[PDB]
Amino acid sequence: PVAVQCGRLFDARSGQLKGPHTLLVADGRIRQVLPGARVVDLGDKVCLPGWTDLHVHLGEQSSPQSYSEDFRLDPVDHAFRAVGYAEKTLMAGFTSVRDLGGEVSPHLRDAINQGLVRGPRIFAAGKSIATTGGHADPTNGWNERLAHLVGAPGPAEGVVNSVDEARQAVRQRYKEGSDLIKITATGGVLSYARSGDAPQFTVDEIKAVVDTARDYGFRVAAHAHGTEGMKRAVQAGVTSIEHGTYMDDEVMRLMKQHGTWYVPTFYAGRFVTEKAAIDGYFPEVVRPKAARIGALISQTAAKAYRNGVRIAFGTNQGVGPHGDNAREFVYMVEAGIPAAYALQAATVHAAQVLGVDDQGVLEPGKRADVIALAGNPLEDINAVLDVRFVMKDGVIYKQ
Amino acid sequence: PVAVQCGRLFDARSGQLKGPHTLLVADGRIRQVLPGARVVDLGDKVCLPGWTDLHVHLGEQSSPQSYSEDFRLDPVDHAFRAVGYAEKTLMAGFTSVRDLGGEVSPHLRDAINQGLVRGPRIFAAGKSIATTGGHADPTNGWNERLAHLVGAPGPAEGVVNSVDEARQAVRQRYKEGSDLIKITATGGVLSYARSGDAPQFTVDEIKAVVDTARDYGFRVAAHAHGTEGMKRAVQAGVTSIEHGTYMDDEVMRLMKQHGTWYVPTFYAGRFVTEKAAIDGYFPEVVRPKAARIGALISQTAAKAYRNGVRIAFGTNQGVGPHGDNAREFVYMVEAGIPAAYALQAATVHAAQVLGVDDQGVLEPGKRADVIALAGNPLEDINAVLDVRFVMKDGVIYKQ
Amino acid sequence: PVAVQCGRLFDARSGQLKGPHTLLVADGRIRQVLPGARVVDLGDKVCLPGWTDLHVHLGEQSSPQSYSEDFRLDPVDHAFRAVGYAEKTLMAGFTSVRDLGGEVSPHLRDAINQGLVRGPRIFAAGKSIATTGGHADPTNGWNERLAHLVGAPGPAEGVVNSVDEARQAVRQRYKEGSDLIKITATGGVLSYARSGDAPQFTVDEIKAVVDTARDYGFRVAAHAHGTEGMKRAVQAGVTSIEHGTYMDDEVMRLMKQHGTWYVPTFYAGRFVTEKAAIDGYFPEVVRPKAARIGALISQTAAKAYRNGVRIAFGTNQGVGPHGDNAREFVYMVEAGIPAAYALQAATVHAAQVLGVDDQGVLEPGKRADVIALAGNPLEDINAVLDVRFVMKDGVIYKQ
Amino acid sequence: LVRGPRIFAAGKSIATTGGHADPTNGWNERLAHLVGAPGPAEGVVNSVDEARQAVRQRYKEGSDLIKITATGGVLSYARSGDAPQFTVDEIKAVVDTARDYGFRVAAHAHGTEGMKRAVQAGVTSIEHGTYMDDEVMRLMKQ
Ligand SMILES: C[C@@H]1Cc2c(Cl)cc(C(=O)N[C@@H](Cc3ccccc3)C(=O)O)c(O)c2C(=O)O1
Ligand SMILES: C[C@@H]1Cc2c(Cl)cc(C(=O)N[C@@H](Cc3ccccc3)C(=O)O)c(O)c2C(=O)O1
Ligand SMILES: C[C@@H]1Cc2c(Cl)cc(C(=O)N[C@@H](Cc3ccccc3)C(=O)O)c(O)c2C(=O)O1
Ligand SMILES: C[C@@H]1Cc2c(Cl)cc(C(=O)N[C@@H](Cc3ccccc3)C(=O)O)c(O)c2C(=O)O1
Ligand SMILES: [Zn+2]
Ligand SMILES: [Zn+2]
Ligand SMILES: [Zn+2]
Ligand SMILES: [Zn+2]
Ligand SMILES: [Zn+2]
Ligand SMILES: [Zn+2]
Ligand SMILES: [Zn+2]
């Protein structure tokens, strides 16, 4: 039973900073929020709920040797690196993350939940679902001999080309122990593929994926850069759109009418624009796509906010260095999004996206996920980079 | 910055021969066409844009040992021969070609674009899409043990039998690096198959191929000898028909209403009729089909021109010897097609077929692809066999 | 440059406790041992070099659900558990370990050497080399369908049946990144096999393994319970024997004449005798062998010491709980081995077994691996269970 | 068809498991399973009969000579650079098999022991000889 003393409380539900408060933590949950048992003093700190990152890849980090690494390294190495990546993510103030690809996160989540290793609460999508030659196709850009020995990927590998294959792929994701579904509706940037915005799913296939996932209680996140694929995914009924680089008035209207969530991922765009100027960092197939698309995400996100599109917090880490996820907040504030809305987008809006009601706000009956900042983030957003107190599920990880 | 001096300019857009002109070439493009910087003199030459051959097979050439060669030779040998074939094609005045089958042309195109080898600009279809036992089926006429070992070809090998397989085949062609799609709608002549004009695709499969290709920005060329398969392909919405031996009034009406392009390929027909009389040149299964169909192409092409069917230039080289592609012009003129129309069918009509607007005519902003002939081709068509100046993308390959 | 102050120094080379001393640590190595720069005080602690455990299995730990776990869990889970196992091992005072089986340790060693995770210095044998149906055969006790699917294990899987297969197996271990070689000369206890002491290698196969390993600079450790297999392995020229339950006067004479090292592993025997009485902990095939064999190790080790056989320190952890490796010391002292010899068997004798001369003794030029104990271990051996200071390669991990 | 010099082509190289010329060195586990362990037809040999079959397969593939890697290298994804990777009884088999088909053998060797083995077996040329010493020089001269 630990009583936390906070000089200033941030109300995620409303978006205002209250006065001094005392939280009572018992059984890993918040019991009382009485204004004003071991005592923890945070008198000179602003108390805020734990943050959520709705777009990470904890089983990888981008490097100059990234592409040559896909044939030399085994998943055990990726797990050994993901241990440190998860610790870095947890220490930065992010008590929960949504992982959007990779077959090590379902195992990292199991390890963290058992107490073997330290890290945030993971909601893992698992393997991605794509079509032939798609953005998430595992055998893109392989020579002929390797492509014959592996064989054509099928629904069990994530690659589908019909309604029945899509149904089997969702069922195989459920069998493999996933918490949600992730599809690539259009092309990408960092893949060894020629296109970056071509429509790669049919409406009748995305509809099948959504219908199959609805039976197993899953939500679907769609990766889309181009207009046509993004429109198809929004019309089929996905839960969130991942980059939306070429969004236009029509697609904004459809998203507003449907209630789809938007995850801008400023950090990935800034990173790829900065690294596209260097020579040898990217392949020659990737550099043009990276230079062309990574520079238009900030304008689209600002326009989406000004048009009334619901925006949640995601960084696409794995591109950027794990543990520097909060720099995204400052980017959002620089793009014109208010600091209070940027803080709400990681606490309550993220919980709405995840479909869980036990986290997000410091209220009785919820999980005890509390962080504390040295300075006030509403006046100076840079204060998000100075975290001094981190508590997850009633356990103090950083004092 | 090279200024080209021409005594007579051929206007592809209109079809008339103008007077003396001066072309200004800079940055690989044409800037000015001022009538009248290094100077190139072609005062005694008729100036004309570069030619396009819309039907070639640069990976092969027909020979008396052609059929026995499919089990002994590797694609590396075919590439080593395609080097010389491409140089011969470029020197004959053809600065662009459309390749309609093979898995060496996508590599040859990449090599040419990088400057490793010399040749024309290639638009490569890649592997062909057929049905089981079709004209482009890779395992036609194989013994039982070999067919057991290789296995039944699937959508990844080009052989499809349903809508979903057709969709996967188009996606696999996109993944393999193709620029367009080629299907065999009926039977052929040079394949180890019993039929020559039977319908081998259903309308619901060609429609799927066309719909899938439209998403990836591809155009579809259809090989058809018989009436029913050709009618199905025209109704499904293909871009061009390849031989059309048994075309009839109805099919002509449908092609005129739809805007489908026609590629007669006189040279292949003449070659197969001449070589069908010899003994041992063709297999016993092929000789009857070759003798029966190769003799009807010239009568159909003349009727198609007289009925108002749009005709583009193609020779089906690989059957004939690479480098003698211009003889087709004389054949066309002998069939009754005017010389001016025969010259236009290789410059502007070919560009319309290819779907590119940067080539075809010597106008500002277009690519600098220029050839020069010793004599006038409008009075004597044989002058197409004497090319003295060849420039491709602002680079002089033949002076 | 950290100077460590010690009240009492233990001389591993001689086996006596000296007086107060001051160690100078720079660059990860020991520079000066001047009797008597940041200062570390350990005035009330007996200083001793870091310990080495010559027999561990860091990729696993025995549990009531151990046998049913070999078909449900993936190596990623084993790595996530090995992280904590390695940290526990390092904190107990063991700065180096020799791993004798499992394909996660070569990855764990790479991760530790890169600084990603904390743990001791690992010398990993990798996959074990056995014969058909042997103790280390991966497919022992599988039903017919599974054995059909996997296929008969070959030299690449560790299972050999001839001289050339043994040579290929050693070469494949070198290719996979191993530091030594481990073979199973006889049967075991914890395997799903009928025998526990039958000879499973021929002399001509062990000789081939030793000869192949000598080229790649490898040392060979042999697992042997029975007399005949142990005699064969000693005669072939292996470096160490792992359990030696049924050793007899002749085999002792051969080991003394050859210089083979002996690793008794008291802890595994005690553990299996205690757990064999329980019902459901072991399979019905394992319980008789465990009850029969695990009760004889202590009498053989005492006789071996009294006969003059060189004995090194090893516990066979993975059977016992990781992190309780020093209780073996007390067992040795209870068996009649002197405390000073038991302490030497983990510092200098272990380094002699490993074939490295940079560790073992606190002398100039050696690695700075230092631990400190609260009490004197020569008078009370129980003081080995109270470690207060742990420094590995000049870095302090426990103060 | 193309212009160039007169080529005498050795073809695929003959190595042992995990050797310098091993085609699957430094591949992850899934790729190594799908390709399978290289055999004598792929150039990787581990016995006398495999070496004989490898020379015969080189002859069948249209080679003009034989090339083996006696020791480790530099540019390969392998840990060693001078370890002995062939036994004398395997190099002798390669040389004896090649002598029937009228082939000459060139040996790649950096380290002393592998180079000595290759010289003693009867190869025609040594390729780098970085760690050659007086003894090996005497053997090569003789
Ligand atoms: C395992 C994981 C798989 C994966 C998948 Cl499935 C998708 C992405 C992805 O959406 N990447 C983006 C990165 C990016 C680049 C620019 C602007 C926004 C985002 C892309 O290339 O378009 C992606 O980045 C990754 C990734 O980093 O690895
Ligand atoms: C690689 C390439 C594949 C290929 C394909 Cl897919 C189709 C043809 C083809 O349409 N050949 C025609 C040749 C021909 C014969 C007579 C009249 C017109 C054309 C045929 O046999 O009907 C064809 O000729 C070829 C060919 O020559 O090799
Ligand atoms: C991965 C690793 C593989 C392995 C191998 Cl290869 C050998 C042993 C082993 O020697 N076990 C001993 C345990 C034991 C039991 C009683 C007395 C001494 C030792 C045995 O069953 O005879 C062994 O215990 C293990 C093991 O625990 O898992
Ligand atoms: C296809 C061909 C295969 C091949 C083979 Cl089998 C051997 C070598 C080779 O001997 N490389 C040398 C390069 C080298 C490096 C330093 C000093 C001398 C030579 C080595 O890595 O030791 C070698 O370089 C190559 C090569 O470059 O590719
Ligand atoms: Zn994405
Ligand atoms: Zn992503
Ligand atoms: Zn055709
Ligand atoms: Zn053709
Ligand atoms: Zn053992
Ligand atoms: Zn063991
Ligand atoms: Zn070499």
Image (cartoon, coloured by chain):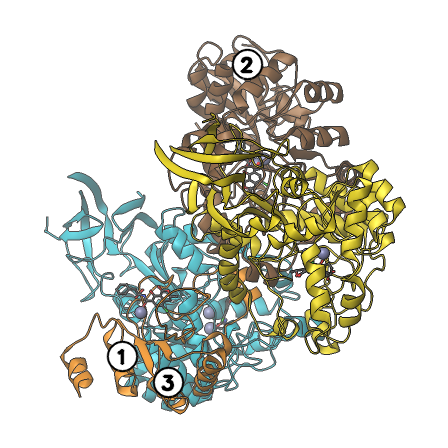
Chain colours: A brown, B yellow, C cyan, D orange
State the separation of the CA atoms marked 1 and 2: 73 Å
- The residue pinned by badge 2 equals A337
State the separation of the CA atoms marked 3 and 2: 76 Å
Label 1: how many residues lie within 10 Å, few (<14), some (14-19) or many (20+)?
A: some
- The residue pinned by badge 3 equals D103
Label 3: how many residues lie within 10 Å, few (<14), some (14-19) or many (20+)?
A: some
Disc 2 element: loop
Q: Give the mark count.
A: 3
Chain letter for mark 1: D
Q: Position of residue A103 (x, y in %)?
A: 59, 48
Q: Position of residue C232 (x, y in %)?
A: 41, 88
State the separation of the CA atoms marked 1 and 3: 13 Å
Any mark on residue C303, and which? none
Does residue D98 appear left or right of residue B254 in this picture?
left
Does residue C225 appear left or right of residue A394 in this picture?
left
Does residue A282 appear left or right of residue C71 in this picture?
left
Determine if residue C320 is in view: yes
Any mark on residue D125, and which? 1
Chain letter for mark 2: A
Label 2: how many residues lie within 10 Å, few (<14), some (14-19) or many (20+)?
A: some
- Viewer-nearest of discs 3 and 2: 3
C33 or A95: nearer the viewer: A95
In the displayed structure, C297 sits above or below C362; it is below
**Mark 2 residue CB less than 8 A from any atom of ligand 1:** no
When asked about the image quadrant of residue C193, the answer is bottom right
Chain letter for mark 3: D
